[PDB]
Length: 211
Length: 212
Image (tube, rainbow over all chains, first blue to last red; front, side, top):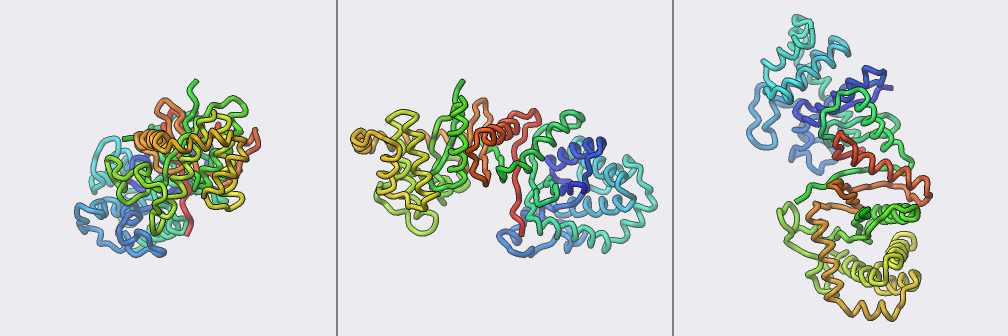
């Protein structure tokens, strides 16, 4: 019934998608937060592979990823696991945490680090002792994240934000402008769903990048 | 008002569907200009991830074969494009009639884009065959017309067909699966496209993944 929304905290377009969806959820439109890792999805070992060969959830939590294809390995893995921990406090706390962290990173330009996770938890009103205890369940949070990454791979998710409407209608939705106004957010969502439900079976609308 | 520019390649059935849609919309007053983008050129290894184009379809010999892989579509597509330019020298209506006839030969009849198909499309389009013959001897002029299309497409960043340039900086690739000829269905589909590109949210991409 809710639309599944795959996101990565790294990604400002995913931030805007989650902001849109949050305001729409205010009006009764159901959305469910799920994770897709850009580091894993774009990883050279996973390129042109029937089956995922390299998992973000196999990497040590404190490991430095380098400056190449894994440069954002550590912040995105840690952000994902903190968000799973927050989501154990229910849907409303999960949205509060995910939005707060997104905003710290993309509006306030803070790194996805421990200080940012802590500020997101207090901005979200989390029970901090419970959040702390859930974060100690690293293996369990990794299993949850791995399940999200598997569901994403089964759909062929390639970027964020990607919305699964159900019924086999799934699409990446990239837009530039932050849209929190309720009326504008509803217009934008209506454009998207209209495009996916058209009996013309629209697959792609995509602007090129000019010279 | 200026027509929408429609970049297509005869090889491509999504471009075919885009041209079929646009022809129906032109029937209600929506303006469209037919232009050419080469998928062979756009996907050529020498052009991959280049600031500037390094290999031009219009630089190639007319009987040259491109060779293995996608390059085998070099000679049909170049030759198809040139015949279309010669057809377009007989006016817009004859150009649409020729483009549609050739598209339908290739995608409905499954005929190769070869000389027999060009001749057949020219007769189906009702061209003046003698003027068409004479224009096809202006190989230099046709190559230069095609190069102008290809450079215009490169300046916009065109990467695939069909790509629609609405003017005002709103340009997008538009890929849809179902042949759409009904006037109302075509108008609704087109309103979807233009609404997406004119939204104040600055939508850049809506794109379905490919399930495993």
